[PDB]
Image (cartoon, coloured by chain):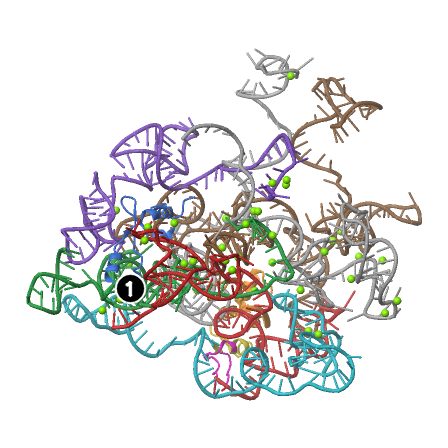
Chain colours: A yellow, B blue, C orange, D brown, F purple, H cyan, I red, J green
Amino acid sequence: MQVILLDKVANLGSLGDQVNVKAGYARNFLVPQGKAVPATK
Amino acid sequence: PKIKTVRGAAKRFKKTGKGGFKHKHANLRHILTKKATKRKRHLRPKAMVSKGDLGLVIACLPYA
Amino acid sequence: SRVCQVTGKRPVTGNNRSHALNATKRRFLPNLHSHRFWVESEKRFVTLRVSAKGMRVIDKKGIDTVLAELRARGEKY
RNA sequence: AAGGUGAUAUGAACCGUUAUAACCGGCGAUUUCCGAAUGGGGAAACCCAGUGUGUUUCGACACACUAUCAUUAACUGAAUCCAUAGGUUAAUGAGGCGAACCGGGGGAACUGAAACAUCUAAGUACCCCGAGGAAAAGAAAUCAACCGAGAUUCCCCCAGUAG
RNA sequence: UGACAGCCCCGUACACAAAAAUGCACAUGCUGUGAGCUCGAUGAGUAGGGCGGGACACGUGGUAUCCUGUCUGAAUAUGGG
RNA sequence: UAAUGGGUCAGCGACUUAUAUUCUGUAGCAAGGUUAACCGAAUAGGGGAGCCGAAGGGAAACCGAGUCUUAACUGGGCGUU
RNA sequence: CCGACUAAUGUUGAAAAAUUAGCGGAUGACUUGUGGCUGGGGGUGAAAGGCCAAUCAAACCGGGAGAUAGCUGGUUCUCCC
RNA sequence: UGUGCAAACACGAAAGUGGACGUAUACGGUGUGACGCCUGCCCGGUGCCGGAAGGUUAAUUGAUGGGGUUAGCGCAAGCGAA
RNA sequence: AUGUUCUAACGUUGACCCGUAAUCCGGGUUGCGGACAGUGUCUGGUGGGUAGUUUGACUGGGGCGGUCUCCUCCUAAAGAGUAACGGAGGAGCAC
RNA sequence: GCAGGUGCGAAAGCAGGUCAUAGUGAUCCGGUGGUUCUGAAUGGAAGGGCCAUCGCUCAACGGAUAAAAGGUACUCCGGGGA
Ligand SMILES: [Mg+2]
Ligand SMILES: [Mg+2]
Ligand SMILES: [Mg+2]
Ligand SMILES: [Mg+2]
Ligand SMILES: [Mg+2]
Ligand SMILES: [Mg+2]
Ligand SMILES: [Mg+2]
Ligand SMILES: [Mg+2]
Ligand SMILES: [Mg+2]
Ligand SMILES: [Mg+2]
Ligand SMILES: [Mg+2]
Ligand SMILES: [Mg+2]
Ligand SMILES: [Mg+2]
Ligand SMILES: [Mg+2]
Ligand SMILES: [Mg+2]
Ligand SMILES: [Mg+2]
Ligand SMILES: [Mg+2]
Ligand SMILES: [Mg+2]
Ligand SMILES: [Mg+2]
Ligand SMILES: [Mg+2]
Ligand SMILES: [Mg+2]
Ligand SMILES: [Mg+2]
Ligand SMILES: [Mg+2]
Ligand SMILES: [Mg+2]
Ligand SMILES: [Mg+2]
Ligand SMILES: [Mg+2]
Ligand SMILES: [Mg+2]
Ligand SMILES: [Mg+2]
Ligand SMILES: [Mg+2]
Ligand SMILES: [Mg+2]
Ligand SMILES: [Mg+2]
Ligand SMILES: [Mg+2]
Ligand SMILES: [Mg+2]
Ligand SMILES: [Mg+2]
Ligand SMILES: [Mg+2]
Ligand SMILES: [Mg+2]
Ligand SMILES: [Mg+2]
Ligand SMILES: [Mg+2]
Ligand SMILES: [Mg+2]
Ligand SMILES: [Mg+2]
Ligand SMILES: [Mg+2]
């Protein structure tokens, strides 16, 4: 899953960075914790 | 309803000019090394259905 | 019922086939799981009974679009 | 319209003959109780209510309302700060029945194969859901064969042919 | 109709008839749905694939095509069936 | 026959029907015959889409009163009168 | 009161399981009234394939249904070759 | 002999329910059948229990080889990338 | 890949709160498990627990025994053919 | 006996297995080689055909399936004095 970090995440990257995470990581943590948003734009 | 052709019969008999039926000879499918060349040669051409069997063949092929 | 709330996938029927081609009736069930979906726009978790395929659909379309489809369909959640 | 008060079915007591006798048609009125049955319950045709009104001669009495679900509103209103869930009220609709035809969800076996398992019977019988006066289908990501056709549906052929 | 009726009776051919309700078909009034027109747009967890089934006259066969329970997964008109 | 069935009577009780196919008879037409659905008020008329027949041989391409077999028949099979 | 070991009778019975003389249990793993629950490859069974409405090695009713029956029975007027 | 409790097990496409508002001195299954004296040898067969080195082995994955097609090389035969 | 740690999916037939007048359910708070368990699709094993079926014929009745195709002789009545669970032998190759 | 090609013989001639009579298995489904005969728009190809050939103690040997043993005294039906 390609996401857009809404903040700095350890091994992931920095705010703005668009990265590919396992769909589970994004759906059950990054997104519900405001730490990222899906790369649709 | 229409009579149904016996399909397996249609794959083994063809009607000739005077109403008889031609067929391929049996015994030329496999084990053939032991069979004499003369015997296999005489099995190659098609043959006519015999009088005894014409009734059976005709019953199987209403639309021939 | 064993119905995906997103896609409408439900059990369907078919045959087991043995090597001897004996046919016996069988069912194919959807890969259903009850999942808590975060709705950022509503600041709420919404639980849906969804197939894995419907999970992928929610990933592709966003939870808001799918919930709107469910509302338009009369499907309560 | 000169007759008439349905039948077994007489009788009785009456109605009527120039037009409110009867009879026939349209539109209306009345339409107990049970039954979806819907105020609650129930061993159908019964038992027992709550609210309003109105009446009482003070004993009482009459009438209307009150099921459930869906949707839409208004008000309200947790855990929990907003809120939501929830609660109540009102509006609108549904419910049940019905012979066949129709679409869909499921779906046999006897039987035939001269036994039997693939195959057959047959997507038939049956169960279930839903609709309409018909339903379904339908305006080519279709065929054709280098020529062309031009949505769907139904009939006759093609053909018991190609497979 | 006391036996078999054109002329006995009721009909029949034919010719007529509605206060009221109602079917349909016309017609033009209220009314909402909005015609023609240029530019533009052209249906994605989809087509397709792997696995299991089912449907196609077609039993997996050398088996196209359709549907999809499961896992995937494009082009998008210069593109696609 | 000491094998079966019937106590008796009356009434009922078992080779049909639809479609396809072949043969016989009969009728029509004849190298031709005949239409289906449908149209039509039409048992008429229209409708020849088709089907069967006048050519066969060969698995087939193909050839054709021939053709197939085979390198080829003195030939042989099926056909032609 | 609950049973049912023996015999006789009865056996188109008084009765589709009884009567008569005897017989066993009789404060218990007893017996009985009312109501309830378990449903057919299913129930229930101190187990006999017992019982599940006089029906049980798969209840009954309706349907598939005119299953199938290489078996048995039966198959109706006359005469001629 | 099974069963550590959301028990084993049973009814049930499931939710659940019985087991049990019980908890190994409990509960299910199996055989034996008061009591007395007892219950011997065999683990090769079948089952069950344990093991896990080595052989064999599913779906899955798709290295490698072969073929069909054809841009082109060719005059033809042919060869032949993606 | 295989360990270990983690929490956020998922489980909870732990606790407490609310809907609520409720040992259902749902929502909240929290603890304990935790990417396991469980479920879907596919797949190997096991599977009389259940189902559909098969289990030949001849035969001095059936069964048990024997036999089942082919060759030679005799029965076979001087052409051919000719039966018995009649009388005697062989083949399913070799080169 | 005819056509083609062949061996032995000087030649006439003989030779299409063996002194003869057993030594065997239909069809289907497929495998291998050859052969443009066919090739679902067309060119190919796949598949099919044709010729040669291979795979059955189908031995119950005209072979019913690719694939099959028992019990019934719990029994049941249709039949036979065959
Ligand atoms: Mg061959
Ligand atoms: Mg009621
Ligand atoms: Mg009521
Ligand atoms: Mg009450
Ligand atoms: Mg049969
Ligand atoms: Mg319509
Ligand atoms: Mg008279
Ligand atoms: Mg489009
Ligand atoms: Mg697909
Ligand atoms: Mg495909
Ligand atoms: Mg497609
Ligand atoms: Mg006598
Ligand atoms: Mg007699
Ligand atoms: Mg008698
Ligand atoms: Mg011809
Ligand atoms: Mg008793
Ligand atoms: Mg007594
Ligand atoms: Mg005593
Ligand atoms: Mg006593
Ligand atoms: Mg017994
Ligand atoms: Mg009884
Ligand atoms: Mg049974
Ligand atoms: Mg039937
Ligand atoms: Mg019958
Ligand atoms: Mg429990
Ligand atoms: Mg004992
Ligand atoms: Mg069995
Ligand atoms: Mg059967
Ligand atoms: Mg026998
Ligand atoms: Mg004997
Ligand atoms: Mg002789
Ligand atoms: Mg003689
Ligand atoms: Mg004789
Ligand atoms: Mg010799
Ligand atoms: Mg010899
Ligand atoms: Mg082509
Ligand atoms: Mg035989
Ligand atoms: Mg046989
Ligand atoms: Mg009997
Ligand atoms: Mg007899
Ligand atoms: Mg006798």
Residue at (27%, 66%) from the top-left corner? B33
Quick check: D107 above or below B62? below
Residue J13 in picture, x, y percent from top left: 12, 61
Q: Can residue C1 be spotted in the picture?
A: no
Residue at (48%, 81%) from the top-left corner? A15
Quick check: F73 above or below A26? above
Quarter containing the N terminus of chain C: bottom right
**Residue sitting nearer the eye, D152 or J60:** J60
Residue at (31%, 64%) from the top-left corner? B31
Residue type marked 1: Leu
Instruction: Return the chain for callout 1.
Output: B
Q: Residues within 10 Å of mark 1 (few under 14, many from 20)?
A: few
Quick check: D39 above or below H27? above
Residue at (38%, 46%) from the top-left corner? B59
Residue D131 in picture, x, y percent from top left: 57, 49
Left or right: where does residue I57 sit relative to residue D97?
Answer: left
The span shown in magenta is A5-24
**Residue sitting nearer the eye, I34 or F78:** F78
**Residue sitting nearer the eye, D12 or D14:** D12
Q: Can residue C69 be spotted in the picture?
A: yes
